[PDB]
Length: 121
Image 1 (spheres, rainbow, N blue to C red):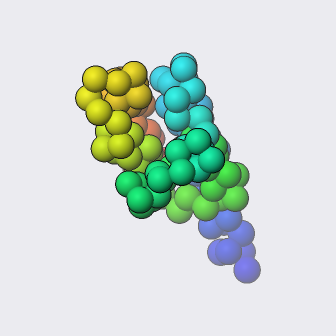
Image 2: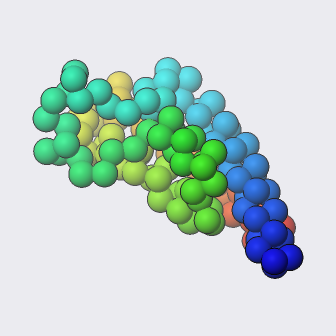
């Protein structure tokens, strides 16, 4: 149908916007602490601590599969990255400190993406 197509073009454009957003959020992690999943070979007990792991590569895979339907779903995953890190790592670690900085610096990027998605529909 012509309706299914028009939906597919909206999803494609949402995907293109969320790709730019992702690139901006990941520039706020210059040390690449959150680039890849936590290694289960190097942290064998990780899944006893964190039930829903997340990272930027895993978000990227989902994005390119057009698996995000709206900005809320994308933000959920971003927030997992941050919140997992702040539980698993103690306050006085380079990891916890990096998540805090990502959270604070990402809030500005997310604040404008919420308006661009409402705006462009």
